[PDB]
Amino acid sequence: EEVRAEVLHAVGELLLTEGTAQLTFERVARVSGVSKTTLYKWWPSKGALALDGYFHAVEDTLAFPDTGDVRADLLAQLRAFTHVMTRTPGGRILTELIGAAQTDADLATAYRQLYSAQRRALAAERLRHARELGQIRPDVDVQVLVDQLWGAVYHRLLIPDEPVDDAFVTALVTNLLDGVCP
Amino acid sequence: GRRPAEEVRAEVLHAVGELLLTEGTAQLTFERVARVSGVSKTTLYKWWPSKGALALDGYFHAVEDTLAFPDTGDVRADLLAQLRAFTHVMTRTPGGRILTELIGAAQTDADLATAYRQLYSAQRRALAAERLRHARELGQIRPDVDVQVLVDQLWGAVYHRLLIPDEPVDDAFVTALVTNLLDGVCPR
Image 1 (cartoon, one colour):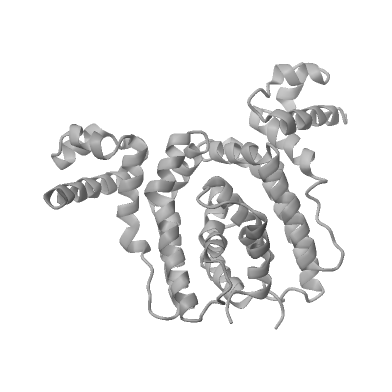
Image 2 (image 1 turned 45 degrees about the vertical axis):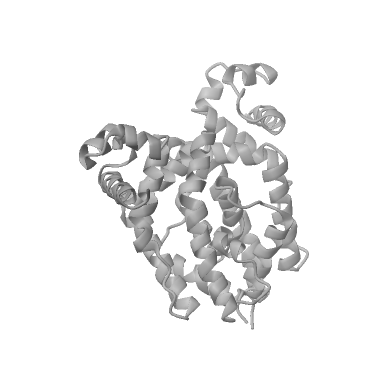
């Protein structure tokens, strides 16, 4: 049934208020409905459950605006993205998961299937619409842009040699849209 | 001192890089390095307080020459040449896996994360930012551009696609990273 909803909802609230440290099947099984091998059938791991619950928890906050101006909408989405990544547990949640995935193939697969593939598709989609209105050159690969935008933020988060601030986010978009050469 | 002592440090670092790149990080041990180099563990422990620091320092010096920045006066050509050597190292060498797994472990090991920056990433960044600032000083990059941001939009973009492979890391990807940035992605 759609009972998968109540679970995701519970997991989402937990993740956004305290991270994954105490995210257990037992606890989730109570706060919501029933475990009964269910959670295990739907979600084979703690990471799977975390990823699924996380995706749906930030889905709306991270949705792309479409007011006709790619610059403004990209800035808007990236700023909502950086707020989630730097002001809520979202950043710590994803970096830990990304970290663990480097030596756990199933978790890596789950990360892409329950979170990253969809996020990238959502970004590429908004980018394609701009590319249609001729706001982005016809020969530009939108998937590359995703890595040069959100990817860049992920990078500073994973390897914090430099801070993720609004100036950073704004330069990301401006450098790309206007180019860095004279 | 810093001569016969630095020579010794270099030999050890060379041994570390050789072992690390052929056998992987799990195989790297102080006992193994000491045996292979002929230098006592006592000395090793003094220079590298941990296995993490040992691996990172050896790794940085093993790829240094290969990842050095050409400085021919053509930022586009030099950037493409460096990103391609970088891509080769990260995808066609054990180096890619070695580094990504250290980045992964660093996510839950504060000390390793600190060593990763001090012995590898901070210096890689400075090397890249330096090449970029040079291009800016020569006028090939707008003077109001923050080169540190560019670092994340080039190498950072590669690391990202490498850490989470939803898309492939090939030459087309590499070339697009540079053209998008240098030429911009908006018409005209």
